[PDB]
Image (tube, coloured by chain):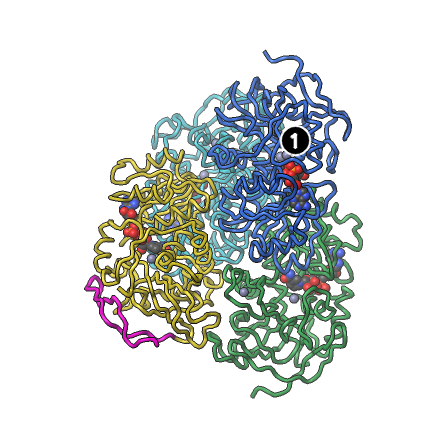
Chain colours: A cyan, B yellow, C blue, D green
């Protein structure tokens, strides 16, 4: 069958206590799939949802997590092109209204009535989770769900971000936070897109990981006292594009100073209460764009999962049990997560 | 002939005393035209060069002014396609190196070795001024030089800025400072480009001018206490594009908040020591680009002067004498300049 | 109620006999609206569907017409954001699969499983017609349905085509067939988009109409023996963009020769068995793009209907009865349709 | 010194007799470099110039060749940033007017007064050749001139062509003629740009070369009777982009049929008297662009030579003597040139 009770990590108040307990199995709405979430990536956005670091409020009590890879155990009556047993991906964008100007254009993420897994919708830190069938990701059969789970928010995000920077092949892309969860996949997406990857990160295991996944230049922010000058030399004038997948505001500000003239600084990371204080003179006389970038749409999901399918991207994951989700968060705020963490909801 | 002495407004120290006295007539270099500057637009950048409001240093003693419209009285030996008597325009970009990556691409303004009239090169607040012949603007014969002078920095700038905002016809463009020197021409360029122009300015004669030149919605910043909300209503979700041609940093910051999702806030105005402190969360979840924009290139100059030629743009100018240049600056810092001021170098 | 029988123009074989008789009222599927089609534009595509001029086969017996403007008299159970009494527009794209790569990207028209009103789906030459609710056009209340009907295929088409030509404001756009049904709206969309409109058409009432709707240069193909030379002079080097809304193949070929270097020739008209024989040398040494363009998507529909709402476009329509649909087709093959014809389904 | 006589291959009438004899050494004009052409690539455009296969006429008597890599032995007085001994590249675009709208925009190749090496200017099939210093390619020191010579017309061309197809990383690019001189470099540029390369060529040594340089799918046009169907399967719907670097018109036409919906067929090859007869219906209902592409500009030259510098592209060259240039042409019309031929002007 589909059971009545399931295991999930749920918190009832912000920065309170994540309880791995038994919660009721959700019922899929007319348009939603019920997905047996096998593995789920643990994004930093989940730490932000728990701490309430962001302006928007979350749907308490909340089962976070928005990188779920699972099998469709049930569907709604109005779900059309989906089978039971198919591989589905719960992304951050649970669904959207698919009618507003933004949605029609393609910008489904920047939509007023966009449902958000792991914030406004009980996400994928649970064995069974519902997801709007139009926005759920189609994961090909015979795919390692643990390996594809981080591609559902980190992969599509950094793919849309690297497309957001208006880079060309051969252009320098500085990925700020290049050994984190999103940065370690941005390095691989950018190399597969043709760019020269510069990496800025620091800590135990960060430079080694960055060199592992194919990065070109690594600049350790805990050792480099002049980061802007270091990325004004490595790059020969600045990085034609910058991807801020850090959780630091000082990194977001330095990225505006080591970007090339006519370059694009994409803001992807969303630290708590951070502002991108950009010098107006330097941004104008260099014609620097500062582009915010939200999670990708269905087209970006298809393209990022296709990059994953060809074996070009491979997020460095450690699969732990869902029981361990408290200890991941306390390991994620301390910057000690090298690559991605994926939780076995079973365990 | 070409005389030995000429009249020019020259200052020897920043925010010192602008002296309208007799200075030697320059000699055109091998690549430069000597232009009998008949009329010259007075930009706010000239007030910034005098006050030294900007990071870069100016070439003291300096004859400012970078909107000169004049006749070519002499040329250099290596100048090719130019006649004596032709109408030339001294723009902010006096010249460029025309060899570096940026110059080759087309971004001649963001070039390391770009010569700048009215900053690093004795500009057009003088009867005779030299200008690199490759970057000088070709003004058609039978043109009102007084009327075309403001198009040489304000016009090409706001044209490149409106092209920088990635707007489409019918999209809302909020021009911040829409009755100033650059804003009053941005309103006209945007309407001729097809956009719905919202205007934000305030003071005596600003709303009336804005309504004169064809603006749609005017929002008076000295009366409107909620500017962001007012431009979130007029526009129905925010302005698809914003052009910051203000000299205020609070305007630059509010423009990041009343821009539409997936909209572009172009920074054109460069107030003294201003920073574009942008909320990272709001910029990311709305995918807002913040694009700096410098003066246009030769293509943008050609296209903006073609817009002027068809009679579509007409900067509201008051032609005073060059003798009056001190009194313009003290009228420009006080925000009391409605439209543009143009100086008769003769007078 | 909703009646059992209705009046419609139906043909049972290609180029057979259009019978205005009583046909059963359709039943809306789970996703479809039943639209009381008040007025319907008569496109040339309907003449092509009747003659079978196109490669694809039509769904016999067929009730053509794909420019229906009507009120929603009934809906399906899975239709979400729609009211009874709302104004809906049956476009050529009746619906789409909204799942394939093209649909996800935004290209809903170039979709393998795209349902097509007036070809593969009983269209809008009938009092009551069904239309997929996701693709039906939202026509604002208090709109002249007769006046908005031609905007449902001609308007969105020529809007997407003018966006397809990668034109800028001030650039020359040669609309081939500028007094026809699509050309007369392309002239107005292009002028509202900022372009200089050149018009090529010929016959009684074509030049007068073209001058009426705001065209700049008219070149009469029945009087001009050198059309390419005439549009190499008017334009000063060729038209930066060309829109082929003709039903002639010689026009489609000449458009490749009077387009500017680096210009774009958009093919919109689809004459019977026509080929765009383009000289490869001239297309390469001038870097001329030849872009085919299909009907617009939901975003283009929204933007074109917004242009119509502001009063910027106004298709020259003559509203006749649906009874007269045979006599329109025989007037449309002879090129004698100046502007658009709209049929009162009531009459 | 610089000698008075030199060795060059010169023909006095079209398809006449190429004579390797002693011709006078040219004198550099005020803006031109005299380049000791060490090695020169032999393009098919040189065979077209000899046969007079193209509409434009050549400058008889003509020393063809437009892929010269050499050292600057002398300069003109108005040449600015150049040294004697530097490595210069004579490309097809010898120079341009650098003042017309196209040149200002960046499209220096599609310019009315563009000087063309190997057609309108004695090219690089000679020991000493002059080249406009603004358009000459800057080849880094310590570069294999024989290996960089084919990058001067083939490399920059196929780079600009792959940028012309509006492809994204992961998209399918079908290179028609993928083992020829331009195709063998288009395969490498496309793989370094991130695309999946499909190759269409045939003959001895073509499939082996294509597999050597990193191609994914090879489709042999002499064995495949259904080329369109084969490239509608390999690609799963058609190639998102096609690069026609063939010398066949049937290939140019089939490329319009095996391109994906919303795909771009770039015409690069310019066979004799060829026309791109494109079905208008299929091009419109699939929104297929057919983009002609001429040699790249200075920015594309810089970017293609940078790709070469990183070791990412490596044209398969055979360096023969200049004495052998007749036997290359008779080997190039027969399609028997696998990769590129480079002539030692010394030999
Ligand atoms: N905008 C979007 O679409 C989107 C999507 C996913 C995540 N995010 C946001 O991205 C942020 C990062 O997510 P993650 O999963 O990569 O987090 P993570 O904690 O796994 O990785 C962050 C990385 O940043 C590095 N870093 C810290 N300070 C730095 C500095 N000063 N300079 C450079 N690098 C520095 C850390 O050492 C670590 O390597 C979070 O705020 C998350 O919410 C945004
Ligand atoms: N980036 C470029 O290429 C470029 C080119 C030219 C000028 N500029 C810069 O643009 C700035 C403005 O130049 P200008 O000639 O338009 O100056 P101006 O003084 O003539 O006009 C400025 C306008 O801004 C209005 N304004 C002031 N505070 C405002 C606020 N809070 N909100 C909205 N509007 C406000 C003023 O009332 C006035 O109408 C200067 O700093 C100048 O150096 C930049
Ligand atoms: N691709 C699309 O999305 C799309 C959409 C709608 C219509 N169409 C096609 O567009 C074509 C035209 O449709 P319409 O409604 O405008 O037709 P129409 O018959 O109302 O107008 C055609 C116009 O072309 C003019 N014309 C004829 N020969 C010409 C020539 N040699 N040069 C210039 N002009 C010439 C006619 O005189 C007339 O003015 C049809 O084939 C139709 O199917 C395509
Ligand atoms: N537009 C430009 O900027 C530009 C630049 C350089 C060359 N060109 C033109 O490109 C053409 C090719 O130049 P090249 O140096 O590559 O020539 P080449 O002769 O060295 O190579 C041509 C290749 O096409 C292959 N081919 C032949 N028939 C084919 C078919 N039916 N289908 C697929 N492949 C086929 C041949 O076997 C060979 O592999 C010439 O006409 C040249 O003038 C254009
Ligand atoms: Zn996430
Ligand atoms: Zn929405
Ligand atoms: Zn200025
Ligand atoms: Zn430069
Ligand atoms: Zn139609
Ligand atoms: Zn589809
Ligand atoms: Zn060549
Ligand atoms: Zn030129």
- Of A274 and B176, nearer the camera is B176
Residue A201 image point, x, y percent: 41, 52
- Of A38 and D53, nearer the camera is D53
- Disc 1, SS: strand
Q: Pick out the residue farthest to the left.
A: B17
On the image, which quarter does residue D91 sit in? bottom right
Q: Which residues are magenta?
A: B1-28
Up the image or down, C12 lies above or below B92; here it is: above
Residue C343 image point, x, y percent: 62, 26
Q: Is residue C290 magenta?
A: no
Question: What subunit carries mark 1?
Answer: C
Q: Inspect this view and state whether residue A1 appears.
A: yes
Up the image or down, C167 lies above or below C312; here it is: below
Residue A60 image point, x, y percent: 38, 26
Structural crowding at the residue carrying mark 1, measured as other residues with C-alpha within 10 Å and reported as few (<14), some (14–19) or many (≥20): many
Seen at 73% across and 80% down, the residue is D19
Looking at the rendered image, the quarter that the N terminus of chain B falls into is: bottom left
Relative side of D23 to A106, left or right: right
Looking at the rendered image, the quarter that the C terminus of chain B falls into is: bottom left
On the image, which quarter does residue C260 sit in? bottom right
Q: Which residue is mark 1?
A: C116
Up the image or down, A24 lies above or below A162; here it is: above
Q: Pick out the residue farthest to the top.
A: C1
């Amino acid at each position: 069958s589909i059971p009545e009770t399931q295991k999930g990590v749920i918190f009832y108040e912000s920065h309170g206590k994540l309880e791995y307990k038994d919660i009721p199995v959700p019922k899929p709405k007319a348009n939603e799939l019920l997905i047996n979430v096998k593995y789920s990536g643990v994004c930093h956005t989940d730490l932000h949802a728990w701490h309430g670091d962001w302006p928007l409020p979350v749907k308490l009590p909340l089962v976070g997590g928005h990188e779920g890879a699972g099998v469709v155990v049930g569907m709604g009556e109005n779900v059309k092109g989906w089978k039971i047993g198919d591989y589905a991906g719960i992304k951050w964008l649970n669904g959207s209204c698919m009618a507003c100007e933004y949605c029609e254009l393609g910008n489904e993420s920047n939509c007023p009535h966009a449902d958000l897994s792991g914030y406004t919708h009980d996400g994928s830190f649970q064995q069974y989770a519902t997801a709007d069938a139009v926005q759920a990701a189609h994961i090909p059969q015979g795919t390692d769900l643990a390996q594809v789970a981080p591609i559902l928010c980190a992969g599509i995000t950094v793919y849309k971000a690297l497309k957001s920077a208006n880079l060309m092949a051969g252009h320098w892309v500085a990925i700020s936070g290049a050994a984190g969860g999103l940065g370690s996949l941005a390095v691989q997406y950018a190399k597969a897109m043709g760019y020269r990857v510069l990496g800025i990160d620091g800590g135990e295991g960060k430079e080694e990981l960055f060199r592992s996944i194919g990065g070109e230049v690594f600049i350790d922010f805990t050792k480099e006292k002049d980061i802007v000058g270091a990325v004004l030399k490595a790059t020969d004038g600045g990085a034609h594009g910058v991807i801020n997948v850090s959780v630091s505001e000082a990194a977001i500000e330095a990225s505006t100073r080591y970007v090339r003239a006519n370059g694009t600084t994409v803001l992807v990371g969303m630290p708590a209460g951070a502002k991108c204080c950009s010098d107006v003179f330097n941004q104008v006389v260099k014609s620097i764009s500062i582009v915010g970038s939200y999670v990708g749409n269905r087209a970006d999901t298809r393209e990022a999962l296709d990059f994953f399918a060809r074996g070009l991207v491979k997020s460095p994951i450690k699969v732990v049990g869902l029981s361990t989700l408290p200890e991941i968060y306390e390991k994620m705020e301390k910057g000690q997560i090298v690559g991605r963490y994926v939780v076995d909801t079973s365990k």
